[PDB]
Amino acid sequence: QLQQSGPELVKPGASVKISCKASGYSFTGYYMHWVKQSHVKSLEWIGRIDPYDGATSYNQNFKDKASLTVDKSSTTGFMELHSLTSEDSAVYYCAREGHWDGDWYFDVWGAGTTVTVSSASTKGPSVFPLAPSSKSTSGGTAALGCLVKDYFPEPVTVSWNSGALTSGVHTFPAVLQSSGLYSLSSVVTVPSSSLGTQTYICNVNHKPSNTKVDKKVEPKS
Amino acid sequence: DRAAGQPAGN
Amino acid sequence: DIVMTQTPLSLSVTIGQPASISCKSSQSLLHSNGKTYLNWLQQRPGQAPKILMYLVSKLDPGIPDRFSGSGSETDFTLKISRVEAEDLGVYYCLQGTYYPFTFGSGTKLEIKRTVAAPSVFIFPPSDEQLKSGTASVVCLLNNFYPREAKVQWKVDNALQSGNSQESVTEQDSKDSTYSLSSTLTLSKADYEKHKVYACEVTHQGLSSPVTKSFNRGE
């Protein structure tokens, strides 16, 4: 019910504007809140906005750092972050303060927007196949995958067969290489007897570099 | 018709 | 700002066993209207937070009844009567009485299950990457428990150090297992100096270490 904008790479001192599109409910009847997650053990409330009249309330820590607006015609909320520092690299959520049983709470959340503050240039990944073979068979099952190497910044999106293959997929958390670039793998287990008839394509989308790659993983001899 | 919420919003 | 303290930091619970998490506020969360604005949230890995309970004790309609909440005005507890696989993640308390909203430290819940041995796979470097001058060799450990595992790379039966990186998945939300990958990275020149590439896997679920090897060029 809430769709947020894509990941952002921002140079230090610049600004960024991220959006939160609402659908399927009365936009002006519910507060839209924003939350900052710096890491897995930190959640901070940034502020809220009343889309009816655009009234805003902010956490004192984010005044002069953030500004909330809405466009009623498109039922979208916006948050602009100003003059970013490295401490502004985080994942940003929007949430609706919904209503149930006469009480109010955050009942719908956006998927989150990753903002990375860095002066480094973006780099798209190169995608290499992890081809199945006798070296990757176990108990009648075969393992195959994609190696997504040397990209900046995070994140990269990996799907299989345009999202039709989800069972048995493991997309590993990226690692930081000594070059400062990232790499990850995505793997899936399938029947070994299926390698002649089935098609396995990993879809790699790295939005900071506008990099979209499809690699068909075929068996090695 | 208007939005309400938990008081910590201010 | 209200300070919200959570205990424990991390928790490991077997499927079907009870779980308990506590939250403490630096001031009373009872508001003038008589409502205690204390919320519990769950955040599964790679997903947004999700409100489980509001007003100390009230469940969101889509939350199973094995979750429950109790508390006073400053001390609160979230209880899971019988933990299931989907209950992994980090739990936060959020106070909504005093401006601004403040979240707790967060409590990590790991799901305990029976030992599961890894299926071990190795992937030689692709021809496409070899033309680019680098060789990445990947060793895959699939669907294992517990999380501790040791993966050693051997090149011509010589133990390797300083040229590999590993990454573990989050705990699986259905079977509570983990997966691990170890990536050995070499230049095309150094890769061509040797013939046999192997990863040796030691894990609690394996009675002896498992070796997956290949010869360069097959």
Image (cartoon, grey):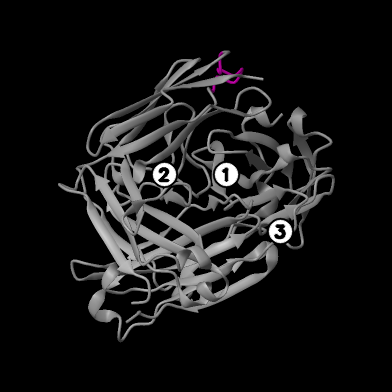
Q: Is residue A46 magenta?
A: no
- Near mark 1 (Cα within 10 A), the count class, few <14, some 14-19 or many ≥20, is some
- The answer to whether any part of residue A37 appears in the image is yes
Q: Circle 2 is placed at which residue position?
A: C61
Q: Determine which of the numbered discs, if any, sits on residue A75 in the image.
A: 3
Residue C120: quadrant of the picture: bottom left
Residue A214 x, y percent position in the rendering: 53, 77
Residue A129: quadrant of the picture: bottom left
Asked if badge 2 and badge 1 are on a common chain, one would say no
Q: Which residues are magenta?
A: C28-35
Tell which subunit mark 3 falls on. Answer: A
Residue C195 x, y percent position in the rendering: 36, 67
- Near mark 2 (Cα within 10 A), the count class, few <14, some 14-19 or many ≥20, is few
In percent of the image, x 59 and y 35: which residue is there? A43
In percent of the image, x 79 and y 50: which residue is there? A11
Residue A218 x, y percent position in the rendering: 39, 80
